[PDB]
Length: 57
Length: 48
Picture 1 (cartoon, each protein chain N blue to C red):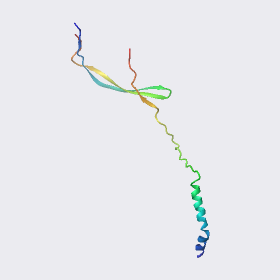
Picture 2 (picture 1 turned 60 degrees about the vertical axis):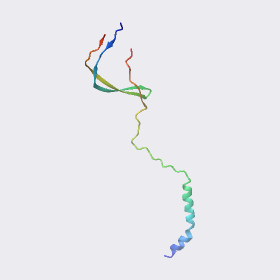
Picture 3 (picture 1 turned 45 degrees about the horizontal axis):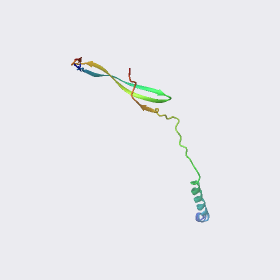
């Protein structure tokens, strides 16, 4: 059971290796592509307000 | 002698609401309109 202390001290180099893991995995580019769901969006339209038809003569 | 016009009295009652919508290549030009019916009222108008 004392072997755990020896293993930790011996394998401590994996700490620096893990530091490299994380601090270059952050450097590497990742992009979680959140979707649009199966249900699709849509806006009304380009709508502009104006005065209606005028009865000229 | 100058003729002169006078009088004229009516009342507005609500009749309806309308939505006109012109279309020109997928873009909408809208307009809300209020239609009022009329009911005449004294004093009568008269061209003097």
